[PDB]
Length: 282
Image (tube, rainbow, N blue to C red):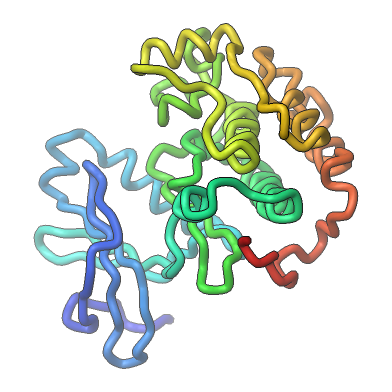
């Protein structure tokens, strides 16, 4: 068996950590243990009306299948007459994006560290035939110890052999704008954008509106500031490649081995990133 199903009364709900069109995430403290969980709450009525059952169900299933230190863990689920609740691990420090603004940009040791954590998280995710499809600084959280915790699998795609979704405009891959489709490489593209954002302080493709943004993406219109770490620049250039089959890290390019072997990660020990002490953020 297992611990009896939990119920709302077992918690003392606190502040709202964030909202979505889909639901609300609130910080809660379980009375019997004093443990803090970030509980995602969804209104069954709203979900049904919006035809999101498949999405919510997929989200819960992907999360249940993940058991890694770089991913928010799902501890339990329960529901009452009107709402569904998902008990997720609480990452106190919030969005990686906050830290990016807070300090402007990351030095080389910090960029390397956090990129390595993300790459390693991606290898794990892709190893299970799962595609995030909306990877970005706002979806990458930080736990109390400053290690990453990736979440929000509401837009995830589970492979079985991935065109029904888009994702945040600035991180969308060109294939999604053209062949109306997506694969593992799509996340790798988002990685390229993220890396670039860690070093430069802003995402690569920026413009007045979505349309302009998409124009630049399909034309690969962007450039590096003259201060950009050379090896990071080289790595980014191998990720922000229009042809999805030529991005460092994808199946056609022989996987994660070559990606992790990149010069930019020279001094990284991949086997125990999570045991390592994250570099102080400036």
